[PDB]
Amino acid sequence: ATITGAQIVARALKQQGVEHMFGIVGIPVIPIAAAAQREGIKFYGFHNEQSASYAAGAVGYLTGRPGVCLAVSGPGMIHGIAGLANAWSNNWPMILIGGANDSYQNGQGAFQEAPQIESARPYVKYAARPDSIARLPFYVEQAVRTTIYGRPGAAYLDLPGDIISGSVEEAEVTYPGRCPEPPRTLAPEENIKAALAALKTAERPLVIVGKGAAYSRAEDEVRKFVETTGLPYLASPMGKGVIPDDHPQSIAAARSFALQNTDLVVLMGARMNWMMHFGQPPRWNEKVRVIQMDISAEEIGTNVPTEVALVGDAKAITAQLNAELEKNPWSYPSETTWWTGLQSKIAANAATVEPMFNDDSVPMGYYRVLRDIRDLIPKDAIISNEGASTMDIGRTVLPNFFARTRLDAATFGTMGVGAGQAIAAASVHPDRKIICVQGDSAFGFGGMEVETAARYGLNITFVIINNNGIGGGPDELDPAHIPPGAYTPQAHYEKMADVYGGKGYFVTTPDQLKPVLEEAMAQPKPAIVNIMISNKSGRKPQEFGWLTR
Amino acid sequence: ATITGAQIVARALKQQGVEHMFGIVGIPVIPIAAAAQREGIKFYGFHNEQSASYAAGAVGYLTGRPGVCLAVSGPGMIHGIAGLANAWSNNWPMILIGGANDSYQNGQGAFQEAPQIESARPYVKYAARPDSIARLPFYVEQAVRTTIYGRPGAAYLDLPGDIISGSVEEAEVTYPGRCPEPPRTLAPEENIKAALAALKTAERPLVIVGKGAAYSRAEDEVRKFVETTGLPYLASPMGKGVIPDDHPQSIAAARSFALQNTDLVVLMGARMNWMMHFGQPPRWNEKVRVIQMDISAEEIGTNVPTEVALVGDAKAITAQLNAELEKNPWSYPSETTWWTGLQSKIAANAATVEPMFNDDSVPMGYYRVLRDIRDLIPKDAIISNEGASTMDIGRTVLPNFFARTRLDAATFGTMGVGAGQAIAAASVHPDRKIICVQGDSAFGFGGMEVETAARYGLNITFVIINNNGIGGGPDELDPAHIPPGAYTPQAHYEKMADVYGGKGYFVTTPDQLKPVLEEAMAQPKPAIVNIMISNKSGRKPQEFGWLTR
Amino acid sequence: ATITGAQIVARALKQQGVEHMFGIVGIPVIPIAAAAQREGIKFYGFHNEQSASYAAGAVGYLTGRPGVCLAVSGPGMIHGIAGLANAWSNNWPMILIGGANDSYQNGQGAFQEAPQIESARPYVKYAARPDSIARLPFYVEQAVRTTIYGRPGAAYLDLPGDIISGSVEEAEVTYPGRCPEPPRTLAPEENIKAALAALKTAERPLVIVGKGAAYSRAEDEVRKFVETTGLPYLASPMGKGVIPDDHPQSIAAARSFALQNTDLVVLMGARMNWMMHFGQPPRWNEKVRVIQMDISAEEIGTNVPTEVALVGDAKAITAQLNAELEKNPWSYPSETTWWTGLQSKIAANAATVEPMFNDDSVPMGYYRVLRDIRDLIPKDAIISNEGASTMDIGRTVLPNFFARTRLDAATFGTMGVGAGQAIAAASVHPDRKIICVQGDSAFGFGGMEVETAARYGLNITFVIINNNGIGGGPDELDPAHIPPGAYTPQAHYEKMADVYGGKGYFVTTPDQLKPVLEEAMAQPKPAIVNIMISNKSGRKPQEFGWLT
Ligand SMILES: Cc1ncc(C[n+]2c(CO)sc(CCOP(=O)(O)OP(=O)(O)O)c2C)c(N)n1
Ligand SMILES: Cc1ncc(C[n+]2c(CO)sc(CCOP(=O)(O)OP(=O)(O)O)c2C)c(N)n1
Ligand SMILES: Cc1ncc(C[n+]2c(CO)sc(CCOP(=O)(O)OP(=O)(O)O)c2C)c(N)n1
Ligand SMILES: Nc1ncnc2c1ncn2[C@@H]1O[C@H](COP(=O)(O)OP(=O)(O)O)[C@@H](O)[C@H]1O
Ligand SMILES: Nc1ncnc2c1ncn2[C@@H]1O[C@H](COP(=O)(O)OP(=O)(O)O)[C@@H](O)[C@H]1O
Ligand SMILES: Nc1ncnc2c1ncn2[C@@H]1O[C@H](COP(=O)(O)OP(=O)(O)O)[C@@H](O)[C@H]1O
Ligand SMILES: [Mg+2]
Ligand SMILES: [Mg+2]
Ligand SMILES: [Mg+2]
């Protein structure tokens, strides 16, 4: 009995817990996709590997096991570097499997001969070309384990065509056991006590809940910690829903005030990177104190010093914090000048946006449109939200009630992830509704993948919030002077639903919003709802712009 | 008087002969696109940088000056690596300009902070981050010159946002003169004589005309050489049209016989790489002798030894060959057993395909559909042809009469280039019709760019030859078992023309072909013609498959 | 009041805990070495950056803060990549600071213009070119912290000449506080319990003590763990001395038997890499069970599956194991079939080597020479031991009694480290004797650094065990057919002591060993002892070669 390299790879992947594979077939990886389907891995054929490789990283975030992207040699693999870099930037587990030319044609100018390991290297924890067919399971298990152990990240496997198509006797192949979940590392008890003692000295304490806490599956421990301590908290964009967004201790609507004035912040799986304005003035106080909880020791003390470091797994360390609070109870008072100032700011920002939610002017505004989207999203739906103002106002208006239910442009700020992340969510969660809310520019980066969603019967509804460009475009184009970020005015993207026999809707007036969105979400194929908005509409005013520089 | 980095870069690019810029704006490169338009560079806003970066390389091939791709920091630049690699593989001049985060935020986890120089490195002749605003023109001229001097190739410029947005006094900036065309290097006269003498010893000589001869603009000298010597010749796929494809000395229809039996080949700007089966058995004779004309000395003698090396520019060396033939006339006899065998093979392959051109069976075949496309392509049109069998049979059926009028997947075999290369051709040749003939899979890699063609008023007609997948897909999909390379059956891609107000046509029967194609090509917006074909249709049988392994 | 980039860098390095800098000056880094000395960093000018860069990584191992290598632009930096790679291979904290050409000359073909960041990249956790003079302390702190937090490793700082020589106002510069010691992470309680439960099921358990335990400074807890449990243990080559090598539970003289027959091993900061034969047959049992203690989660389960993963700091995790043994006491019985077999192999291997220690044949053998070296080494000396058989037999014959007192070719198997590691050890431990024991080939990789040791008054004695080549060479060279690994027969390397006015000794017969070594170790300048041995002498025979 013999077996091919392709069949060994597919068996090993399934044994290691891979359940989802996204890519595009061609020389030399056709038999890998075929073998993956026979092993029961779900294979999705995309229209571009760029989108497929973003889907793979999203699987890693959602499941804690790497999604796999399968790409042909040369340009196929290079298209997939996009997803390597997005997983690198977000510390998400993901594997790109790239075919390569037959090894005995190296140097000859073989079909799609390319330095693929060197191209992947900057973005991966692990890059390997297996030396022989019979050792393939060694490399598969090592790749999988390296993506999920330590700080999670990306890996690249380089498979020459002759390793894929060649055969060995089955008896020559040893398969490792399934890589177990990594141990959930703990902080020293002295550091646990030091974190809690420091909290008790703060006049204006703040907890930030980030997507590291979501990735760790720490949501029960984090909610218990925040409720026991009574602390104000802020969710990062993909930390939304770790604690339900309607929780009374959320100060999301006073975010700028909270960061500017806190004297002590607890970072629960969140970085002091650009998203948090580096922890630095003018957005933070120059003397802010930091308790930092991260699996990555090297991240501790980036940009601003850390007073108490909690290095390890967020679920395990937050459980240590909760155990120590049970031993030595403490909570932050419910009546303080901090709470009063936070509540004043929340109420003022609520009053500012309320008229915008209720403005029926045409062309419509973001808040008016997102109001009706919000009121029709099931509470356990997964939201894929991508764009500039479409995503930023979507972040504030569309709540999440469960962890890991918002997928957006994330740390790398990537356009091109929307449909791929929606398809990943549908594959992981076949029983949920997926709502994809994209700006019109965002939609165009991967718009062909609406047919992919349709072909695999995925429960995704596509909503486009269209202002004619990248932050808007004019109503009529001057052919001699097309703005660099404009598109065809009133582009009818919803006609793309006719490609696969779905329903497309073109919305311009507020009386259309509720009936159209309700009907669209009920369709047995993915509907596309193309909603025109004013090119003057934008977010509620802020003292500071989001891009600190 | 002061000037920004963005304005300096745009002025320098225009001074160096850059006329075409393709990309997507965003932080930090918005002011570069604006300044490029003010300087009179044509800027095209794409839906994905992947397609834009392929457009830039095509400009390099068509014009001999680099096309420029403009990309934002991080994922924008990484999307554009695709075009770097395609230009690397084809030795085409091309520049990717990537924004980068502000330099004073390095190390902080800045927005879209990424190792962009290291990501570009494997594919570029030149990668630089300018050290200061006032030296920007030094780097622009050095990048341009490096892409077109020597063996042409790709370059990457890394521009931190503060170099783009900062200003200096105009008096601090020196601008180099426009980089002149590189000198057209000559072979030693002894080698010229040796090449011609070797030709006179051959019993079965063959000339191969490749896209290096096209790039060199050598078409007048090459045609004169082939006609003076009376030699049989074969065009490579993008060498088609250097000599008009209806020339009586073409042996294209006997290609396999010609390569298998020639005893001496003249490579005029063509590599012995995978496209030519490495010059090795079983597709070539083991003792074949090679005269090799290439600008790259390092390419000489790859895979098979070269008997006479002609290193330098193809136009200049072919002129040397023609001058020596005028001094010492010679021609290959018109009546030889070689010619008789070539003509026998041509006639047999003509007889094999003639019934296929005339078969009206539905679902239709490739040859029947391509017959009617061929008969409506203007003789000076530019053809963009991409796919597997759509491109390979398009290569044989659709003739080219002028040099540099076919753009296809080229050396890297890339899917994703079709629409971008058509847009590049339209930008370079505003007075010509561009016909883009894509397989259905090929179409989906960059299908959103039909709106880009429409928005800029480009004279492109999109034809899709649709067999439901990558080499075909079934007529009905089993939801539990979707073939990895299949798409939605009878996908109505022509409805994408409704996005921008163009006309879409759905063709299934042969009586539709001529009226539909005629009307589509006459439209003032880009039409999409979606032509269904049998999933059993394929190319005429061959003794060997194209992928030697 | 203004300050240069060079002065900022030196102040930042000192503040971050850097104490030792090794390198060679020239354009553009001259002012950095001067500023370093003014800050009280110890600077050593070497004869080659290659040796200097190995010294920097050894400081990191010995101290837990990176040593720094200072190199000029272009070839200076490239010579120092050797030390980046050695630190990478051993997970030692180390910084290479390379000068670069002036930034405004990039692209021009500037003096020593080179792609230095890309050259360092494969071996470093961190590589940065500071964007501006005022942010230099940001990069220094970030580089230091990255080398010592998590799995320790190397960093590269790329300093253009105009960042070094340029100035800013002092008020423009902010200095981060000294990087605190890294947090010492712990294993889940259920894993601590599972480790101890597994030990109680084992018929033939074994502890392996590696240089990760030494780097962690876990020696007190490791000794307590091994003594409490009564387990047999094996030290890795640089794990020697974490427990004193004369400890009764060491099974070093039964190494192959122990690895072949153990059914459950506790890896205390040691890898299943080539040095442990990948944990695989034929050197290990196919069904061996593994409890693995390592700070690197990604290392867990390499080559063979791990049954209990103890991810975190070795000192902290061993303290966890000790605390649970206090609650639930257990020890391995002192009379078992396993102990009886281990002791039988120990006694047989002892009987095999005893006549080699007492063999007075000339030319001499390794064991007879190393016997007299051993008996003169002070118990708290640092040993630098490098070569092939010189190092491999030195490993078994020369005991260590304290942690971090043996420095050898380590995980990368590097020749070129011996003098640089001895100089590093002298700098870290000015109160100790440093003894450097090298094969003749190893000596030649960095032999000019004996003058560096003399110039800085370091308490180092250089011993060369000389068999005329790489594993030996002939007594007479056929001048037209020189064997690729041979050197001049009876090459008088000890005459190099005359370069700096030291004492060189040439030894051929056993009566000379003891008086020569005693006198040499007492010299006020570094002495060189060049000891000839037979080119037929070799190590004790083994069933298996070390290179699996
Ligand atoms: C790969 C890549 N390329 C480009 C960008 C730059 N970029 C933005 C943020 O840097 S965001 C946006 C779309 C906004 O346009 P939109 O979706 O229509 O949303 P809206 O504001 O008009 O509502 C674009 C193109 C990017 N981030 N990533
Ligand atoms: C970037 C990238 N990704 C994938 C491939 C693999 N690949 C092919 C050649 O290796 S070709 C083809 C389309 C054929 O399908 P098609 O267009 O519908 O043409 P047709 O034969 O059915 O007529 C595909 C997907 C590739 N080359 N480059
Ligand atoms: C940088 C580098 N270059 C070469 C080697 C290969 N190499 C050895 C590996 O095992 S070891 C040794 C010397 C043995 O010769 P020696 O010192 O005289 O010792 P001895 O056995 O004769 O007693 C040499 C040269 C190396 N490891 N690193
Ligand atoms: N299991 C885990 N426990 C704790 N931290 C984790 C875990 N997995 C990832 N992380 C950390 O979570 C942090 C998430 O930061 P970031 O992506 O910036 O979050 P956000 O964008 O939500 O602020 C990263 O620094 C990462 O190392
Ligand atoms: N100006 C020039 N003169 C001669 N050769 C050139 C010139 N420019 C590029 N080339 C060479 O032309 C060759 C084209 O080969 P290739 O791309 O394989 O052609 P094809 O695909 O048409 O066979 C390359 O090796 C390249 O170095
Ligand atoms: N503080 C620490 N605690 C635990 N493990 C550590 C620590 N520092 C380094 N390590 C680990 O120690 C291991 C040492 O293995 P190695 O260098 O192979 O040792 P040896 O050569 O002694 O077998 C490395 O895998 C490294 O990740
Ligand atoms: Mg928009
Ligand atoms: Mg097709
Ligand atoms: Mg020797």
Image (tube, coloured by chain):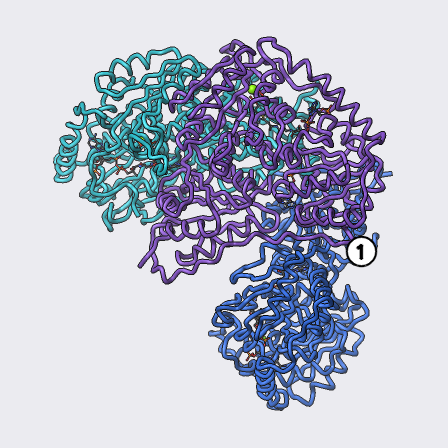
Chain colours: A purple, B cyan, C blue
Q: Nearer the viewer, residue C442 or B369?
A: B369
Residue ranking furthest to the right: C1
Estimate the x, y position of residue A422 in percent, counting from the top left.
51, 32
Is residue B64 in sight in this rendering?
Answer: no
Q: Is residue C83 left or right of residue A456?
A: right
Residue bearing the label numbered 1? C41
Q: Nearer the viewer, residue C86 or B516?
A: B516
Mark 1 belongs to chain: C
How many other residues sit within 10 Å of disc 1, few (<14), some (14-19) or many (≥20)?
Answer: many
Location of residue B256 by image quarter: top left
Q: Nearer the viewer, residue B40 or C246?
A: C246
- Report the amino acid beneath label 1: Ile
Estimate the x, y position of residue B476 in percent, counting from the top left.
30, 31
Is residue A398 in sight in this rendering?
Answer: yes
Q: Is residue C210 above or below residue B233?
A: below
Q: Is residue A535 above or below residue A527?
A: above
* Residue at 72% from the left image edge and 69% from the top image edge: C403
Badge 1 residue CB within 8 Å of ligand 6: no
Q: Quadrant of the C terminus of chain A?
A: top right
Q: Is residue A55 left or right of residue C354?
A: left
Q: Is residue A61 left or right of residue A497?
A: right
Q: Is residue A111 left or right of residue C288?
A: left
Ligand 6, what quadrant? bottom right
Estimate the x, y position of residue B268 in percent, counting from the top left.
32, 36
For the residue labelled by badge 1, is the local secondary structure a helix, a strand or a loop? Answer: loop
Q: Quadrant of the N terminus of chain A?
A: bottom left
Estimate the x, y position of residue B84 in percent, counting from the top left.
48, 35
